Amino acid sequence: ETGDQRFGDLVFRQLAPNVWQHTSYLDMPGFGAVASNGLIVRDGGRVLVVDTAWTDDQTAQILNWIKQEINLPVALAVVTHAHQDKMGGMDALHAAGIATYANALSNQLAPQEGLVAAQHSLTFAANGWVEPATAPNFGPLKVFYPGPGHTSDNITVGIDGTDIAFGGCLIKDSKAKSLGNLGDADTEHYAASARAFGAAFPKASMIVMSHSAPDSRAAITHTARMADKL
Ligand SMILES: [Zn+2]
Ligand SMILES: [Zn+2]
Ligand SMILES: [Zn+2]
Image 1 (tube, rainbow, N blue to C red):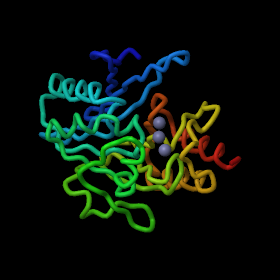
Image 2 (cartoon, protein in one colour):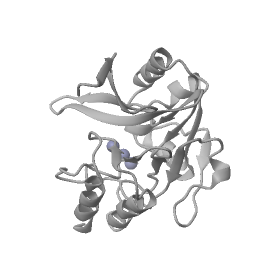
Image 3 (cartoon, protein in one colour):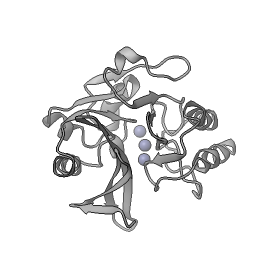
Image 4 (cartoon, helix red, strand yellow):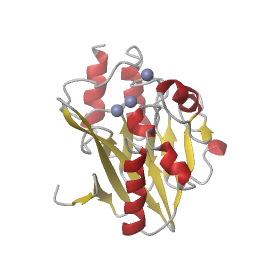
């Protein structure tokens, strides 16, 4: 936590020369603050964002941090499924003029989940890789749909040119006691989807997730083993 920066209500952690983790918190009374993590990636003269914060105001703070610390324009944001911790700040991205992308299924589910859809839809091949025409100019972001797990629409993102891959809410840390929120989950296919994420990015050694600090690939294997028991 030495290299963690407090900026407003958020926390930023540099993971690589060109990759930062953003963390926002939603306080639930009686339970305490709950963190949600996303990514900020520099790609030459532009910035790419993975996931919003819980709220519009927090997402505006992410943009403010990028402006202060990097001072380059945000080209696009990818959001990894239609839940509040990943898409709760879509209006802030749109007000800033940032192009937003999500799984077509995320955009179709967003209204039913109390959310605004992204402005562009990603589609995927039968083996999970994104159709490149739907992800134009994504630079180092390599988007992979691993199959239904935490939700039916959850997607994951490898950062090409680094050893980092983002599992979102599909992957839990190697010490996790449970798979988190399973209310929208596909318990039948979860284990295969977790393993497919590991197989898509087989050389990623730092696994970033939504609700725990970055971990080793033991996050992937532990998650799959928990899901085997479902
Ligand atoms: Zn979720
Ligand atoms: Zn739901
Ligand atoms: Zn979550």
